[PDB]
Image (cartoon, rainbow, N blue to C red):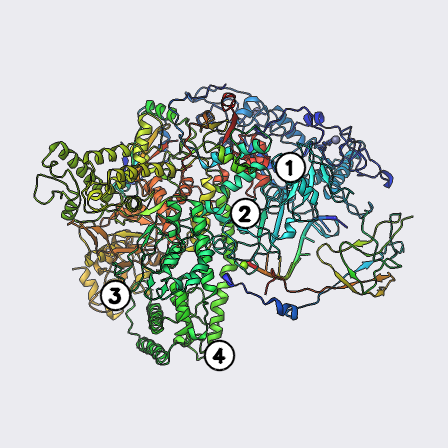
RNA sequence: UCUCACUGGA
């Protein structure tokens, strides 16, 4: 790029400044005299109309006159026109701002309406924030609508401070499209607002007016907010299109401009000549409408101006609004060169960093490398071979950017390569490239692998890198990007290759492992029966590509050399390993060979399965990568792959219907088991017929029957499945694949053998699409499971067509859910990316945005990386008091806490010494304060926690290196142990400033890890069980320091984008008491909007008593919402004309009871027996409640509860009483509370667990009561006595913030989001969601994850604009004229520099002195 | 201004390197190497400029200065040599 | 056969397994303006310009329907002047190659001399193909 | 300290911006019946003095604007009596690092 | 010479 190199100084961008034109500035810029509405080709000849395109504007190829800026089509930016708008027209998007600024000004003067005479205007002018400041001034200047000349100041009312006069009234203007009607308002004075009048008013609005209105008189001029000279883009913006001759097909913006210039001639000829003062008003509106519909055509002037032949318009808001729009299509990732796309295929003979490229791509994918003396012979040999082979050359780019095009000329073996040229050689081996599959979803979604050129055009990959790509071999497609510069190759090769990626940041696990065929093969292989002959041991030992040439000793040599093939697997596993699992009863004498034990590459015992060689938490690949590094891991994969490959090729593994059919009598047992299941459903149906079903609270009788049917059905299904699975024997191959874990599950074998089970649609079982029945083959009103959707036989025996239709529904439901969830998870993905795009971590380990706003002080509160964090256990947090004291307590001045001299060689002379006893009791009290601290942190007390480098692994590594013999006591000095503990405790530098803020930050950050380290390297541990030496201890502490300061977080990771992708992956895997989860939950939380579809909450009981049922009944009754509709059937108005004796005989006694002043209107309310036993409500309580809630015009009268009708007679206490009394008794029935607060719906009395520490030392899973409910009013349900309001919980984060403060709202947001994601079963790391939840709660409220919040924050314009709001926010930042700092990722994507992050987050400068030094 | 250079005490950054800094250093020295620079250590018969740069940075022998941009717009300088390439 | 991919006896592919012909057809038009102006199908030359070799053309710019076609051959010769001779032939398909099979020389309701080409192409089941 | 039982007139609140510096509070009895810092999701808040604010902003190369914020009408902010410009330390428990400091300006 | 429409695959 850029032939004819010149002398302009070169830089990169720092300023992005917006603002509006002057018309005089356009007259300064342009070189145009535009009047010809006829466009181009003067008298239809290949020549130049000088009115439109080329009045020395841009021309096209082979006709170069472009005011000496010829350059062909390329190398010449076009230049701008202009328009002589006689009548001034509006600017269409700015009209909302025009209304909102004409509410602030007295007309025809320009003065502000409301000034610092107003105290609120004074206080509101202190906002140094332009947009919200103008918003507040607009809210203040919508108040009063008349220019007040003599104004009383904020001192006293009787004196009248003057200002500019002209006390005219501001008319109320309401918008009508291109028309703003000024109706002055006595005397409705509707006046069409002159553009020339408001022109003059804005030309008179002044300096302090603009700047106190948040606008810039240097740049942002609301009198420049009116179009009166419009510049015209060049033909290098609007091109032309031919039909091999210019007959048809020019451009739409060209014809828009010809249209508006024709409308300009229409406004011209009626002002140049006669003036129709009711028809020259439309001489403008044509021109105004056309220049307005140019820039925007979604206006409230609903005539679209649909252009000819059915194509409506081609406008610029439609050009700029994204998704095939201009910004989002050409600016944030486009179609590229140096590209390759094909189908994929597999092979295991290749390796993990290898991809098999076709030879004919290698003949056309190429690389322009410079002429180098280091292989000038081979490069000249490539250009001597020629472009028509594999090892050839395509171009020879010369020294000044000149491509030698080889083959089409006559000398394909031409010139020796001059130094300074670039030979464009083709692809050769071991240039690793980028290789991605769309959709891209995480860090691992792209990787790099070396090239191994092959025939038969596919793209290879190794079969255990096809797992994290989420590809498969159904012809799913992957792309190929070849990096181009030398440093680009270096960057991709040193970062983006697969062994660097292996441990995954997603949920801190390995993302790869071993997959189906290799996996089941290694599952059969490491069985003990796999005895191997001699020459096959020879063949596999050559097959390992890095054999040591050592024929191993045969474990069986009795007569004959045999091998238990675990041992010949062990020659693949390299040195320095340990693992141990202890599955159920694996104590060193396994009757099952399940578990593991490895030493240095000797499998001691145990099968190899997915929880060793796959993706597992205690992964063997994980331990290999931590103990060695990536290239040793990469060779591990090759060894295990090709070893199990050869053993599978010459053993074989098949499957078939023999793996499906169970034995005969057990299939008979299966069928009678489902028969007893239908016996159970038959008994509970016949109990439903008698209607005696005790419906527990939460559901009615029918759904309380339904949950019992579904539960008994699926319980019977899985019991019969277990019966089948333990029927089957070892030679069941699909059972062997199940214990492999390649595909399938116990549910899969259960489906294929015992029974299919239960179809479903949308959570329910099958409901009647007809009336009363699902199928015409069924009776009407059937709640047998056979019509409600049970299926009787498994896939073996078949499908009756009713079952086939049920199952067709149950599958088409799943196709519904994929065909909607791909769309909504794709939108939620792109929203989260464009939200958290720029959050990196800077050098002082603090987390910043594009605008320097600090987001997290230490990333993840420690600077510990998801590329490193493992899971280790605690030891302190459990244990009894006496057991823990026996465990760690050391004293010589006691009976049993002594040591044994078989550990310490100097154990005799150590006795009784207080000079060490003070140190020992220091350490023990340190760890007991630590124990209290841990039980302050973690309430439950589980022990596996995401922490950095494994202490337990590192001491056992020192054991298996330095040969601890457990008979000689050790030479370790106890003072040296304590001193090394202290010195390494003061050694873990994450923060490196020497003052008290930094030191408190460092100590408070790594507090918990240092607690763990001292709990582990305590004295009795390192003596009794790890039993180290002096050299072992020193090497252990050296290793802890070394790998901890290796595993501290580096600066430069785009932790925001990587966090967004790592929470955006496991949302894809989601599917669908009845409280929701899934993509509706995620969308309800990120789009924080108030109408949440299940706002539930939870209370606990009083902290005094444990599980008291009567008191829990009291709390739920006292909270439980109770209205009069809930308690009534018959609300009756009678007219009993005797208000001292009831004409109905039921109520003789009651008035003379009451009299132991009225109306003849008997007002009767029935209560039912069901409701006043549903709540513990007394009739006297209810009557006194009616009393104390009305108290005005009613005589309360009860009835008897012991008599079985509950009647509330009333009359009226002092005739046209019923006409208003019917609305009154409505308001009784459904507008008066009786118990609790509102929004207390279905209240569920649950008896959960309580995982508490014991009052004796241990842990206790305790019973108590915890209520469940599905309402929200947190302030009012909180204040009720009888609960545990310090431990209340709601999901409704809006009310949680507004009730309990923003930081507790953030923390509850976090627990909510984490638990509703990990309810699926998947996992993610803490820190990615931590960064996300903090950017949610940083701006002060809860910023919604949409265009309502963060994309309406005060951040940079061009970073903000690329989420489909292009015209709005671009015209906004042109109105306020903002300075964008160019400190943003998307900004440098748009403007083409290095992104100012990561490997763009520093400089590189050449030294002068070390150049002299190193020679 | 350039009133923004901390001297070589109280440098709050690391005495290590990072992967990204390592990547840019390796690439930049490789760009010089493939752009016909004087090498500083002997070839091992090696025309592989990534491997050449890794040989050079085995022993702190690459003549460059890093500018760690401090998080306010200021910066520190850094010799390549005083880092610890432990990884 | 990791991840469902299947493995193929190449010898039966020689014996005929999944062997297949393929039939695409073309079009070309001597176009019609509004002023009754007819165009021409004849053997074009240099008198939008290509550089495809005229080696398999006919008298009237056609191709005989039984010859192997390859590379970037000019498919249908076409010329049109305005009152010059343009390069209105259409070159070959960049994505496929084969044998021209069947040529008919027809017209429409209003007399546009209309010639067509169907192509036959053998295709053998190669490795990167989906079954 | 001024505590209403149920209501205070909004037009009565036009007497509030009256004098520097003595400030009148406004509190619901019912909302303060239980503590809004006793809740186990509420982290403990601790004040800062202005010279230590100068200390902090010189340590972190920061200003007033670059900080994580809060609104003045925040419930525990009105529990603490926080006015415009301050800095409040927040020390919260966690999982992967035990303890961690948090700083909020009060705009 | 491409704009749009509708199919097709993942
Ligand atoms: Mg697929
Ligand atoms: Zn020019
Ligand atoms: Zn005025």
- Secondary element under disc 1, as helix, strand or loop, is helix
Q: Residues within 10 Å of mark 1 (few under 14, many from 20)?
A: some
* Disc 2 residue: CB within 8 Å of ligand 1: no
- Say which residue label 2 marks: A450
Looking at the rendering, the quadrant in which ligand 1 lies is: bottom right
- Between marks 1 and 3, how big is the CA–CA gap? 107 Å
Residue holding disc 1: A376
Mark toward the viewer: 4 or 3: 4
Disc 4 under 8 Å from ligand 1? The reply is no
Q: Nearer the viewer, mark 1 or mark 3?
A: 1
Q: Confirm or deny contact between disc 1 and disc 3 (CB under 8 A).
A: no
- Look at discs 2 and 4 and give the one toward the viewer: 2
User: Mark 4 = which residue?
Assistant: A776
Mark 3 → mark 2, Cα distance in angstroms: 87 Å
Whether marks 1 and 2 lie on the same chain: yes
**Marks 4 and 3, how far apart in space?**
47 Å
For the C terminus of chain C, the quadrant is: bottom right
Nearer the observer, disc 3 or disc 2? 2
The alpha-carbon separation of the residues under discs 4 and 1 comes to 84 Å
Image point (54%, 59%), residue name: A473
Residue bearing the label numbered 3? A1206
Q: Quadrant of residue D9?
A: top left
Checking the image for residue A459, the label placed there is none
Q: Residue at x 74, y 39 (%)?
A: A414
A1264 vs A169, left or right, is left
Sequence-wise first label, 3 or 2: 2
Residue A109, how many percent across, how many down?
60, 24
Pointer 4 chain: A
- Residue A100 visible within the image: yes
Crowding near the residue tagged with mark 4, few <14, some 14–19, many ≥20 C-alpha atoms within 10 Å: few
């Amino acid at each position: 790029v850029g032939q004819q190199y010149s002398s302009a100084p070169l830089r990169t961008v720092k300023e992005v400044q917006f603002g509006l034109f002057s018309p005089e500035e356009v007259r300064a810029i342009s070189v145009a005299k535009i009047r010809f509405p006829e466009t181009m080709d003067e008298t239809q000849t290949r020549a130049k109309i000088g009115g439109l395109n080329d009045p020395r504007l841009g021309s096209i190829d082979r006709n170069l006159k472009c005011q000496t800026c010829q350059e062909g089509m390329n190398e010449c930016p076009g230049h701008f026109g202009h328009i002589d708008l006689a009548k001034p027209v509006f600017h269409v998007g700015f009209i909302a701002k025009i209304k909102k600024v004409c509410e602030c000004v007295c007309m025809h003067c320009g003065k502000l309406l409301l000034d610092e005479h107003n105290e609120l205007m004074r206080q509101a002018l202190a906002i140094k924030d332009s947009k919200k400041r103008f918003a507040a001034i607009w809210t203040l200047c919508k108040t009063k609508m008349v220019c007040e000349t003599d104004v009383p100041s904020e001192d006293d009312p009787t004196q009248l401070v003057s200002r500019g006069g002209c006390g005219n009234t501001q008319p109320t203007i309401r918008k009508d499209g291109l028309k703003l009607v000024g109706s002055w308002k006595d005397e409705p004075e509707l006046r069409v607002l002159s553009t020339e009048e408001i022109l003059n008013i804005f030309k008179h609005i002044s300096v302090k007016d603009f700047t106190s209105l948040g606008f810039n008189e240097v740049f942002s001029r609301p009198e420049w907010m009116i179009l009166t000279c419009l510049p015209v883009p060049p033909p290098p913006v609007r091109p032309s299109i031919s039909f091999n001759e210019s007959q048809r097909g020019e451009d739409d913006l060209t014809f828009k401009l010809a249209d508006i210039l024709k409308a300009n001639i229409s406004l011209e000829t009626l002002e140049h000549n006669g003036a129709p003062h009711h028809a020259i008003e439309e001489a403008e509106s044509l021109l105004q409408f056309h220049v307005a519909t140019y820039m925007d055509n979604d206006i409230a002037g609903q005539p679209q101006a649909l252009q000819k032949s059915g194509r409506p318009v081609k406008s610029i808001r439609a050009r700029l609004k994204g998704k095939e729009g201009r910004i989002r299509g050409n600016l944030m990732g486009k179609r590229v060169d140096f590209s390759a796309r094909t189908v994929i295929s597999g092979d295991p003979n290749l390796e993990l960093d290898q991809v098999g490229v076709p030879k004919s791509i290698a003949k056309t994918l190429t690389y322009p490398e410079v002429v180098t003396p280091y292989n000038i012979d081979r490069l000249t040999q490539l250009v001597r071979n020629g472009p028509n082979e594999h090892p050839g050359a395509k171009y020879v780019i010369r020294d000044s950017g000149d491509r030698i095009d080889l083959r089409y000329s006559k000398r394909a073996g031409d010139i020796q390569l001059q130094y300074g040229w670039k030979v464009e050689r083709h692809i050769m081996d071991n240039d690793p490239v980028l290789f991605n599959r769309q959709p891209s979803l995480h860090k691992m979604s792209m990787m790099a692998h070396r090239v191994k050129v092959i025939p038969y055009s596919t793209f290879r990959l190794n079969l255990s890198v096809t797992s994290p790509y989420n590809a498969d071999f159904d012809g799913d497609e992957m792309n190929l990007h070849v990096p181009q510069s030398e440093e680009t190759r270096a960057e991709l090769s040193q970062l983006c290759a697969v062994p660097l990626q292996i441990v995954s940041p997603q949920s801190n696990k390995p993302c790869m492992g071993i997959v189906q065929d290799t996996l089941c093969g290694i599952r059969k292989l490491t069985l003990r029966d796999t005895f191997i002959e001699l020459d096959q041991v020879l063949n596999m030992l050559y097959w390992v590509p890095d054999w040591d040439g050592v024929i191993p000793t045969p474990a069986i040599i009795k007569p004959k050399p045999l091998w238990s093939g675990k041992q010949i697997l062990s020659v693949a596993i390299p040195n320095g390993i340990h693992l141990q699992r202890f599955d159920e009863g694996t104590t060193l004498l396994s009757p099952k060979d399940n578990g593991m034990l490895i030493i240095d590459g000797q499998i001691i015992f145990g099968v190899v399965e997915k929880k060793t060689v796959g993706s597992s938490n205690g992964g063997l690949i994980h331990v290999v990568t931590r103990e060695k590094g990536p290239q040793v891991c990469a060779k591990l994969f090759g060894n295990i792959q090709k070893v199990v490959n050869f053993w599978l090729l010459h053993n074989g593994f098949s499957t078939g219907i023999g793996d499906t059919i169970a034995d005969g009598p057990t299939m008979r047992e299966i069928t009678e088991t489902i028969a007893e299941a239908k016996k159970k459903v038959l008994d509970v149906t016949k109990e439903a017929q008698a209607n005696l079903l005790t419906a527990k609270h939460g559901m009615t009788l029918r759904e309380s029957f339904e949950d019992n049917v579904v539960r008994f059905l699926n319980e019977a299904r899985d019991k019969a499945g277990r019966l089948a699975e333990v029927n089957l024997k070892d030679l069941n191959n699909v059972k062997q694949m199940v214990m492999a874990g390649s595909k399938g599950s116990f549910i899969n074998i259960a489906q294929m053998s015992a029974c299919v089970g239960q179809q479903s649609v949308e959570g329910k079982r099958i409901a009647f699409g007809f009336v009363d029945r699902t199928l015409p083959h069924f009776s009407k009103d059937d709640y047998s499971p056979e019509s409600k959707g049970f299926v009787e036989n498994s896939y073996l025996r078949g499908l009756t067509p009713q079952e086939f239709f049920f199952h067709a529904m149950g599958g088409r439901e799943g196709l519904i859910d994929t065909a909607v969830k791909t769309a909504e998870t794709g939108y939620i993905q792109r929203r989260l990316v464009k939200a958290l795009e720029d959050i990196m971590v800077h050098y002082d380990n603090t987390t910043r945005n594009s605008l320097g706003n600090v987001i997290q002080f230490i990333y993840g509160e420690d600077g510990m990386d998801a590329a490193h964090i493992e899971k280790q256990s605690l030891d302190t947090i459990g244990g009894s008091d006496a057991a823990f004291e026996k465990r760690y307590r050391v004293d010589l001045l006691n009976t049993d806490h002594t040591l044994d001299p078989s550990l310490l060689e100097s154990g005799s002379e150590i006795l009784g010494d207080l000079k060490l006893q003070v140190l020992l009791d220091e350490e023990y009290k340190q760890l007991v304060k630590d124990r209290k601290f841990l039980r302050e942190v973690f309430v439950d007390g589980e022990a596996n926690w995401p922490l950095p480098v494994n202490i337990r692994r590192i001491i056992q590594n020192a054991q298996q290196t330095f040969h601890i013999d457990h008979t000689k006591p050790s030479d370790l000095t106890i003072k040296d142990i304590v001193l090394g503990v202290k010195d390494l405790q003061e050694n873990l530098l994450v923060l490196r400033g020497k003052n008290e803020i930094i030191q408190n930050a460092q100590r408070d950050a790594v507090t918990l890890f240092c607690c763990l380290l001292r709990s582990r390297l305590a004295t009795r541990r390192v003596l009794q069980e790890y039993r180290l030496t002096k050299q072992a201890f020193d090497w252990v502490l050296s290793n802890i320091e070394a790998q901890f300061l290796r595993s501290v977080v580096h600066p430069g990771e785009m932790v925001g984008v990587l966090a967004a992708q790592s929470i955006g992956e496991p949302a894809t895997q989601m599917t669908l008491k009845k409280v929701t989860s899934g993509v509706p939950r995620l969308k309800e939380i990120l789009n924080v909007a108030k109408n949440m579809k299940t706002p539930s909450l939870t209370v606990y009981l009083e902290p005094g008593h444990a599980a008291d049922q009567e008191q829990a009944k009291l709390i739920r009754s006292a909270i439980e919402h109770t209205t009069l509709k809930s308690v009534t059937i018959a609300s009756e108005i009678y007219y009993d004309p005797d208000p001292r004796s009831t004409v109905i005989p039921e109520d003789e006694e009651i008035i003379q009871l009451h009299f132991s002043q009225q109306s003849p209107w008997l007002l009767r309310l029935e209560l039912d027996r069901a409701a006043m036993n549903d709540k513990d409500l007394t009739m006297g309580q209810v009557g006194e409640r009616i009393k104390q809630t009305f108290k005005n015009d009613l005589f309360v009268i009860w009835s008897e509860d012991n008599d079985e009708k509950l009647i509330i007679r009333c009359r009226v206490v002092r005739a046209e009483e019923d006409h208003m009394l019917k609305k009154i008794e409505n308001t009784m029935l459904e507008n008066i509370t009786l118990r609790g607060v509102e929004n207390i719906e279905r209240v569920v009395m649950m008896k959960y667990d309580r995982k508490v520490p014991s009052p004796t030392g241990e842990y206790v899973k305790e019973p108590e009561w915890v209520l469940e409910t599905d309402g929200v009013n947190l302030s009012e349900v909180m204040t009720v006595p009888g609960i545990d309001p310090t431990r209340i919980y709601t999901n409704s984060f809006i009310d949680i913030m507004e009730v309990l403060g923003i930081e507790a709202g953030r923390a509850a947001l976090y627990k909510e989001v984490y638990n509703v994601i990990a309810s699926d079963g998947s996992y993610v790391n803490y820190r990615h969601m931590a960064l996300l939840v903090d950017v949610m709660t940083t701006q002060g409220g809860l910023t919604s994850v949409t265009r309502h919040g963060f994309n309406r924050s005060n951040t940079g314009a061009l970073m903000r604009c690329s989420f489909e709001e292009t015209v709005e926010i671009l015209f906004e930042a042109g109105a306020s004229a903002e300075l964008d700092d160019c400190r943003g990722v998307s900004e440098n994507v748009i403007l083409g520099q290095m992104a100012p992050i990561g490997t763009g987050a520093f400089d590189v400068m050449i030294d002068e002195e070390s150049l002299v030094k190193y020679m | 201004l350039k009133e923004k250079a901390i001297p070589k005490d109280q440098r709050a950054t690391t005495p290590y390197m990072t992967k990204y800094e390592r990547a840019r250093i390796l690439g930049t020295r490789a760009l010089q190497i493939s752009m016909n620079a004087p090498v500083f250590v002997d070839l091992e018969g090696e025309t592989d400029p990534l491997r050449i740069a890794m040989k050079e940075l085995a022993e702190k022998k690459i003549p460059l200065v890093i500018r760690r941009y401090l998080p306010d717009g200021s910066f520190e300088d850094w010799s390549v040599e005083e880092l610890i390439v432990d990884l | 056969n990791q991840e469902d991919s299947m493995i193929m006896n190449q010898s039966s592919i020689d014996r005929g397994l999944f062997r297949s012909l393929f039939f695409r057809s073309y079009m070309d038009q001597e176009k019609k303006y509004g002023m009754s102006i007819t165009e021409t199908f004849e053997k074009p030359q240099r008198t939008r310009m290509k550089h495809g070799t005229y080696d398999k053309l006919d008298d009237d710019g056609l191709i005989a329907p039984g010859v192997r076609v390859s590379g970037e051959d000019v498919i249908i010769g076409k010329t049109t002047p305005i009152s010059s001779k343009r390069d209105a032939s259409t070159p070959l398909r960049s994505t496929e190659n084969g044998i021209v099979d069947q040529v008919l020389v027809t017209t429409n309701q209003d007399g546009l001399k209309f010639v067509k080409v169907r192509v036959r192409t053998t295709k053998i089941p190669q490795i990167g193909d989906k079954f | 300290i001024f505590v209403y039982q149920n209501n205070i007139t909004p037009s009565a609140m036009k007497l509030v911006p009256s004098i520097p510096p003595a400030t009148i509070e406004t509190f619901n009895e019912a909302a303060l019946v239980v503590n809004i810092t006793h809740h186990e999701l509420v982290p403990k808040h601790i004040r800062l003095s202005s010279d230590e604010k100068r200390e902090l902003l010189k340590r972190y190369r920061l200003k007033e604007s670059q900080l994580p914020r809060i609104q003045r009408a925040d419930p525990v902010a009105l529990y603490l009596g926080l006015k415009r410009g301050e800095v409040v330390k927040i020390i919260r428990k966690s999982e992967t690092s035990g303890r961690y400091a948090s700083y909020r300006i009060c705009m």
